[PDB]
Image (spheres, helix red, strand yellow):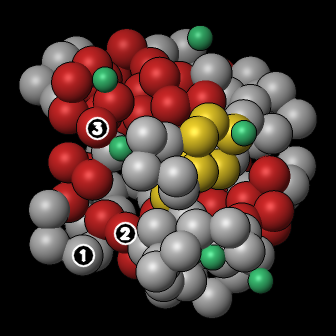
Amino acid sequence: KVFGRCELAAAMKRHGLDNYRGYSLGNWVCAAKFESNFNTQATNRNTDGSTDYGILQINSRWWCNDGRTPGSRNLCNIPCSALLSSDITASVNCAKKIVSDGNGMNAWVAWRNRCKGTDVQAWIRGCRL
Ligand SMILES: [Cl-]
Ligand SMILES: [Cl-]
Ligand SMILES: [Cl-]
Ligand SMILES: [Cl-]
Ligand SMILES: [Cl-]
Ligand SMILES: [Cl-]
Ligand SMILES: [Cl-]
Ligand SMILES: [Cl-]
Ligand code: NA
Ligand SMILES: [Ru+3]
């Protein structure tokens, strides 16, 4: 599923992301934009052999199991394929663990490089949330 901007914002809010660990809703939508372009099916291989899955490009080295990432953990206790679903519940529950891990949203390199510090409220402008 390719979400619309406000559509994803509403979904994220419903699932308890707005101000989760103090990150406003615009932060999460901005991260999703640059990680996946709002595409639940997005996958991208990393240089280390792990792969990133779904709207928030969650990484098989720590977070999910994809069966092909040696020496890796599955801290969200989920198959990585569950992160590609039209229903974002698994992705959000797993993001909640990630953001709680100590470095906040800096875990998402695209967030640090493209969203951090910016006017992220622009990403929810116009949405009825
Ligand atoms: Cl957009
Ligand atoms: Cl915001
Ligand atoms: Cl891939
Ligand atoms: Cl594996
Ligand atoms: Cl599995
Ligand atoms: Cl959903
Ligand atoms: Cl990242
Ligand atoms: Cl980046
Ligand atoms: Na893994
Ligand atoms: Ru839902």
Q: Nearer the viewer, residue 62 or 105?
A: 62
- SS class of the residue under badge 1? loop
For label 3, count other residues whose C-alpha is less than 10 Å away and answer few (under 14), some (14-19) or many (20+): some
Tell me the quarter of the picture where residue 117 sits. Answer: top left
Pointer 1 with pointer 2, Cβ within 8 A? yes
State whether residue 41 appears in this view.
yes
Q: Residue at x 43, y 40 (%)?
A: 47
Q: Quadrant of the N terminus?
A: top right
Q: Cα distance, mark 3 to mark 2? A: 13 Å
In the image, 57 versus 105, the foreground residue is 57
Q: Is residue 24 above or below residue 71?
A: above
**Local crowd size for mark 1, using a 10 Å CA cut-off: few (<14), some (14–19), many (≥20):** few
- Which amino acid is tagged 1? Asp
| Amino acid type, residue under disc 3 in the picture | Val
Is residue 29 placed above or below 11 in the rendered structure? Answer: above
Quadrant where ligand 8 appears: top left
Q: Which residue is mark 1?
A: 101
At 74% across and 22% down in the image, what residue appears? 4
Image quarter hosting the C terminus = top right
Q: Is 109 displayed left or right of 80 in the figure?
A: left
CB at mark 3 closer than 8 A to ligand 7? yes
Answer with the quarter of the image where residue 24 lies.
top left
